[PDB]
Image (cartoon, coloured by chain):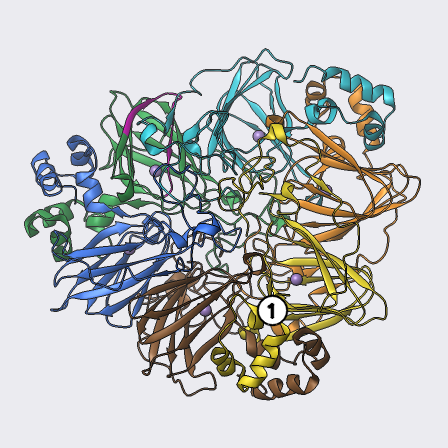
Chain colours: A green, B cyan, C blue, D orange, E yellow, F brown
């Protein structure tokens, strides 16, 4: 997990030419002000008119620099009816979330030694879920109304590996012949999938 | 921070005679079912008719055994108008929270090397805050309506050190002469304070 | 990363009814013998006549109990010509490997904040590679001969999330409608993919 | 706990304009000399003519830069007869100490899940005590002579949250109305307490 | 470093048939009493009439079970005039110590990338030293009186690798031919050294 | 163990005047190229015509900067017939290795609480071994042909404490009188040993 802090506060210095280190260098405390432990970036709903039908409003250290060194971060996800936060993975953290409105099918997948078990449940307002570090998971809006959830992570920068986008639209894309052997389908099927993720989202 | 997990899942075995270890032993996976990564315990508001005027609904590993080994936990706090979650400390975690309804004055205090600075702000619906590991902090409902927040921690068992209750109503209470030297007031003042925390809450 | 050790040795007790904890309980030192720090399980090549065209011979704590608490483990992967270790993820570790024979295209994919960059190179005998914790990666045999590599991990139980098998053949499988929204293709395409992973491998 | 070291030595560069990071940047090894692993700052007794009747001589990374990255630090506390190291907390470390001279009442308080138990004992020359990470604790000189102890921590910068001073004399002070609700006493009592900690110590 | 604690207290259960885990299982809190955070085992001087001319009084988790899970431990070392705590290593911790009486030559050795530098200084009453995790170090009494020091570690079980005893008197001893190649001397010299450590101390 | 990473990649900036921190600062991602996760430095055998009769080809972060922050590193050791990697220690990591060719006697020594037990075995092609963090260990070529092994570590910079060289040829050397008390032999024997390690290797 993220390294523990070695002082009370260390607000991230995000200017482009700052020296680079594991995580982020910090602003001098003299330049921090009173406001760094607070944020209002998750107050409004994100735009759900996207191919996935969901919008992620991030609140990691790049968006909330006061989280630097503190080992935590959050995000908000809004969903149009039938929208999905597609099968994805956080490489460096466990996720713990709460559904605020609507009805979401939440699915968590065990690794190979857990027999690739799929745990899935319809989670409603006020109900919570937990996603173990590095496991594949997804959310699907099964209600007729817009849904939204707010989650927390045990990292300032959990990272996100979107499975569909990484598999078919990385930069540059995984060679077709690699994907035909791995997916056990012909090249035409692989190219059809790639054509849907050519936009970069 | 909490030790990282060494397998996908390890639901806590909470029976009274289970062997004791750092954290908790786990139920055999065969006895876990499909439901351990989910909870509905924070769906309803807690009873705010208490001396503090707030109610904490806990969702640590004792209440949500599926969090065992995953490094995270949550809780919900409800506040009557003018109620407080009094100055307190979490010995083993950073807290990250969101106000869901109402208006809360949230205050975070730096340690001695930070000049004991008090950072405080009125946090409203959808706005977030972060409390660094082990620092004193509090919340006070400044609105005319009931307020509530949901927070996450970077520990399965953050712990809570309530300052007023620990100082004046521990078991057994800190001797009066220790408290008169520390608080710089006469014994009568110390005894008055102790009389308010004799109930254990 | 894995918790550090609190003593010299703690060989894993793998009997089925042993108490369950994070990681594994250990055999009494009196029952360990001289041989637990050694293994010969990776001496021979695995059977590459599988759908993927590769075979993984594991040497994690379940196969090498002397690794318990030491924070490390290994495995060997053998590849038939044109075979692949398909796009996969290790949820709890970084991997560091060496190609022993043959020619392998090794690809590592960055997360979303790294623009989903694909780093790929043909790695030959004696050459090494490193896969950051939790990122998607794969290997493909581009030579005309059988290839093999031996890798190490910074966990006693890294875990493996096989992307194709988890996406299309979990237990039970991810609903088709979830996968059609996520993959942006019709149900018939999703069902074709599922039919290839119905065997459990 | 503090991050582990990634090299033998990394003496802290404490100049005011050094770049800021978690912990401290280090002096080039060429500028370190032979003396950084040693100190004589705890050889003499501190001045106990203070309001608390005790004096803390710190030996954290700010006073002993050679501790940077090594995960440890110390301090010495001297006590006039009847003096106290008041109820306080270390946010980022466990403390382990030894009484060198005199008789000290040492008290350690459990958190809420430990029923706020007060463990207290008179500790004399050569006797030791341990304070778990983040718990409230104090020391009181019950002998007729000056007493002193030397303690170690499992952090280069444990931090110190003095309860009385933080509660009544932070900068700026916690509002009176917050403190009257939390302490369950009238404003006049709160103002009396605040008047004793207006000096900043 | 040692895993962080997941609760306030977890006194080690040291009975011989207790289940074995990383570190130690804990006594039920009901069986702990008030005394586990304290010890008087380092109050008296150890017997320095040994081949090394020094005596180590240990206060690790085997001798102080209340340290279990807290990440710290101590020990006391007493030295006859001209006695030594021979070149040794702690595999799992940094050491931080204070000389209480006498004059001790304290030497710390850097690793190969630090050019195997020897840092050494005569440390007197009240003066401190720090030994980075896993580096070779020693102490030698250069005064005419008995000397003693008390040290702390950042582990409940640091471990001790005595160089001379391990090299020449392990169980069973390292073969002579291995040692003649490594030490670049004839077999007769190696056998002479082995004869001095045949007693097991 | 090494601090976990807080981003995907952080290639070490090894220029001499780069700011110094725990571990290494990183190159801007814009200056990294595609090649940092790969290396060919262990493809060839090292020169075994040395006093020890073995050659270590290092692949730590100084030689493979792409390992920075990832918690892993490797090395290759080649051995002439009868050559040794002498009794040594890695202060900051566990080692896990595989013999690639030849026959090596591999010995691992327990600490004092493990009764200084010597575990030793002849390890051949494809067979593996594990060395717990900070314990003394060695390898000796018992075959008639050149032998070689490739090992991995759970640190980007494990460090190496060569016992013979550190004991008798540090800079500057440990005083003779310290070594005569510790080794229990006369000064002439100590000086003979020192004369063999005066070259610095
Ligand atoms: Mn997620
Ligand atoms: Mn709180
Ligand atoms: Mn892999
Ligand atoms: Mn203290
Ligand atoms: Mn020592
Ligand atoms: Mn080695």
Picture coordinates of residue B12, whole percent (x, y): 43, 31
Picture coordinates of residue B29, whole percent (x, y): 34, 33
Q: Quadrant of ligand 5?
A: bottom right
Seen in the image, is B30 located left or right of residue C148? right
Q: Residue at x 76, y 57 (%)?
A: E46
Span shown in magenta: A120-133
Does the magenta run of residues contain D116?
no
Picture coordinates of residue D34, whole percent (x, y): 69, 73
> Which residue corresponds to mark 1?
E165
Looking at this rendering, what residue extends furthest in the right direction? D144
Residue B197 falls in image quadrant: top right
Picture coordinates of residue E69, whole percent (x, y): 57, 43
Q: What's the magenta bit mostly, secondary-structure-wise?
A: strand
Does the magenta run of residues contain A124?
yes
**Callout 1: SS:** helix
Chain that bears disc 1: E
């Amino acid at each position: 997990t993220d390294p523990d802090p070695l002082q009370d506060f260390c607000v991230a210095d995000l200017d482009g030419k700052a020296v680079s280190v594991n995580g982020h260098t910090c602003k001098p405390m003299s330049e921090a002000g009173d406001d760094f432990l607070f944020s209002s970036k998750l107050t409004k709903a994100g735009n759900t008119s996207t191919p996935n039908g969901s919008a992620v409003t991030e609140l990691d250290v790049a968006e909330w620099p006061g989280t630097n060194t503190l080992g935590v971060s959050m995000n908000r996800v809004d969903f149009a009816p039938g929208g999905t936060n597609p099968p994805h993975i956080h490489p460096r953290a466990t996720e713990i979330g709460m559904v605020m409105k609507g009805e979401l099918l939440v699915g968590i997948l065990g690794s190979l030694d857990s027999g690739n078990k799929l745990y899935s449940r319809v989670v409603r307002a006020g109900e919570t879920f937990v996603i173990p570090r590095g496991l594949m998971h997804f959310q699907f809006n099964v209600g007729k109304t817009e849904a939204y959830m707010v989650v927390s992570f045990n990292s300032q920068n959990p990272g996100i590996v979107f499975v569909p986008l990484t598999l078919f639209g990385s930069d540059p894309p995984i060679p077709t012949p690699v994907l035909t052997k791995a997916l056990r389908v012909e090249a035409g099927v692989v190219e059809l999938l790639k054509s849907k993720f050519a936009g970069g989202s």
